[PDB]
C-alpha cells in the first residue's frame, strides 16, 4: 500500500452518509454492522493490527488470544522454527516428525505436548470505546459509504421505495469503487517493490523463508565476484 | 656455487605459475565462476524437476 493507515473514529462515515436525505435513518448501530461486513468482504490485511503473543501448550492444545482473527505464523518459542498446517487426522490420539498446528475456535491444536509457541496474529484496531476504528483513506471511506448506501437501497428496493434505476446506479458505483479500493490497499509501495524484487531475482533460489518468519524474504541476494 | 660463497639455498625448489610478478591465476581459478553458475542453474533445474 502506498498510503498510510491513519485511523479515525467510525462516525466519520456517518458524517458523509447522512448528506444523503434518504440515509437519515442510519445509526452508529447500523454503521458498526455494515462496517464489519465491509471489512471482512474486502479482506484487506493492511486494515488489521499485527500482534505477537506467546501461549503455553498443555497437551497438544493451547488457549488462543481473545482478539485473534487470523494467524500469520506460529513458531516454537525456544527454537524459532515455524509450524505448518496439520494434515494428520489422528494428531494426539495414540495407537496400542516436524511440528504443525490447527486452530478452530479459542483453541490451537499443535502436534507438541508441552512447549511455548509464539503466534503472530491480526486483530482489529479498536477505539477508546470498544468499537472498530476505520482508515481515513477517502477511497476506503467512499467505498464503505457506497457499500452502506447499496445495502440500504437494496432494502428500500425490496419494499419498492426506490427506483430500479437508482439501485442499478448505486450497484455500478459501488462495484467500481470496490475494485479501486482493492487495488489501493494491495498494490505495493516502492519499499514493498524492493522487497518483492529481492524476492524475485535470485541466481540461487531461496525456498525456506517459511522456517524463519519470512524475515529474509525481501533480502537481496549477493553473489561474490570471482 | 664455485665463485659466489653467498649462493646457497634449502632443499625446497618450486615455481609459481604467475604472470609478471603477480599472484597466480590458476586453471581452477579461471574455471571456477563457470562451475558456480553451473551449480546454480542445475539447482533451478532440479527444483523444476521436483515440481
Image (spheres, rainbow, N blue to C red):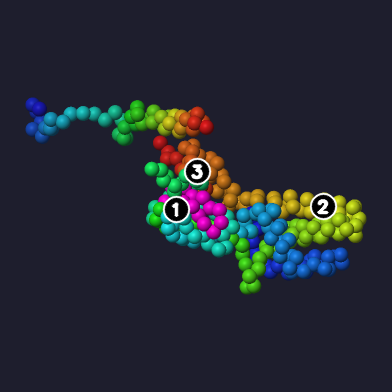
Q: Which stretch is magenta?
A: A99-112
Is residue A68 left or right of A179 when viewed as pictured? Answer: left
Work out whether disc 2 and disc 1 sit on a shared chain. Answer: yes
Q: For label 2, count other residues whose C-alpha is less than 10 Å away and answer few (under 14), some (14-19) or many (20+).
A: some
Residue at the far bottom in the pictured view: A128
Most foreground residue, A31 or A134: A31
Q: What residue is shown with label 3?
A: A89
Mark 2 / mark 1, whichever is N-terminal: 1
Image point (87%, 67%), residue name: A21
Residue A114 locus on image (x, y percent): 39, 56
Gap in Å between the C-alphas at discs 2 and 1? 48 Å
Q: Is residue A213 visible?
A: no
Q: For label 1, count other residues whose C-alpha is less than 10 Å away and answer few (under 14), some (14-19) or many (20+).
A: some
Work out whether disc 3 and disc 2 sit on a shared chain. Answer: yes
* SS for dot 1: loop
Tell me: residue A217, above or below residue B10: below
Q: What residue is shown with label 2?
A: A171
Is residue A103 left or right of A132 when viewed as pictured? Answer: left
Task: Kindly report which numbered mark, 2 or 1, lies closer to the viewer in this rendering.
Answer: 1
Work out whether disc 3 and disc 1 sit on a shared chain. Answer: yes
Q: For label 3, count other residues whose C-alpha is less than 10 Å away and answer few (under 14), some (14-19) or many (20+).
A: few
Residue A50 locus on image (x, y percent): 56, 59
Looking at the figure, which quarter contains the N terminus of chain A? bottom right
Disc marking residue A60: 1
Residue B28 locus on image (x, y percent): 35, 29
Image point (82%, 68%), residue name: A25
Q: Chain of mark 3?
A: A
Gap in Å between the C-alphas at discs 3 and 1? 13 Å
Mark 3 / mark 1, whichever is N-terminal: 1
* SS for dot 3: loop
Amino acid at each position: 500500500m502506498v498510503n498510510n493507515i491513519n485511523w479515525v473514529k467510525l462516525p466519520v462515515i456517518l458524517d458523509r452518509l447522512l448528506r444523503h436525505p434518504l440515509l437519515t435513518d442510519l445509526n452508529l448501530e447500523t454503521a458498526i454492522q455494515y462496517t464489519l461486513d465491509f471489512i471482512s468482504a474486502m479482506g484487506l490485511p493492511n486494515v488489521y493490527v499485527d500482534k505477537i503473543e506467546t501461549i503455553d501448550i498443555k497437551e497438544y492444545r493451547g488457549e488462543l488470544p481473545c482478539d485473534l482473527i487470523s494467524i500469520n505464523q506460529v513458531r516454537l518459542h525456544k527454537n524459532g522454527i515455524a509450524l505448518r498446517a496439520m494434515t494428520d487426522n489422528f494428531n494426539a490420539y495414540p495407537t496400542h516428525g516436524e511440528p504443525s498446528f490447527k486452530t478452530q475456535g479459542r483453541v490451537i491444536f499443535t502436534s507438541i505436548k508441552h512447549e511455548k509457541v509464539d503466534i503472530s496474529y491480526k486483530a482489529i484496531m479498536l477505539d477508546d470505546e470498544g468499537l472498530p476504528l476505520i482508515p481515513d483513506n477517502p477511497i476506503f471511506l467512499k467505498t464503505l459509504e457506497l457499500y452502506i448506501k447499496k445495502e440500504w437501497f437494496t432494502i428500500l428496493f425490496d419494499m419498492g421505495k426506490i427506483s430500479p434505476a437508482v439501485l442499478n446506479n448505486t450497484q455500478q458505483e459501488y462495484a467500481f469503487k470496490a475494485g479501486q479500493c482493492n487495488n489501493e490497499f494491495v498494490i505495493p509501495s516502492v519499499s514493498e517493490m524492493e522487497a518483492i524484487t529481492n524476492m524475485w531475482n535470485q541466481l540461487i533460489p531461496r525456498v525456506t523463508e517459511f522456517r524463519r518468519g519470512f524475515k529474509n524474504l525481501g533480502d537481496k541476494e549477493y553473489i561474490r565476484v570471482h | 656455487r664455485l665463485n659466489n660463497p653467498s649462493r646457497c639455498h634449502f632443499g625446497i625448489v618450486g615455481s609459481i605459475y604467475n604472470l609478471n610478478d603477480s599472484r597466480p591465476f590458476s586453471l581452477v581459478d579461471m574455471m571456477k565462476p563457470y562451475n558456480y553458475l553451473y551449480d546454480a542453474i542445475h539447482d533451478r533445474l532440479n527444483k523444476a524437476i521436483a515440481s
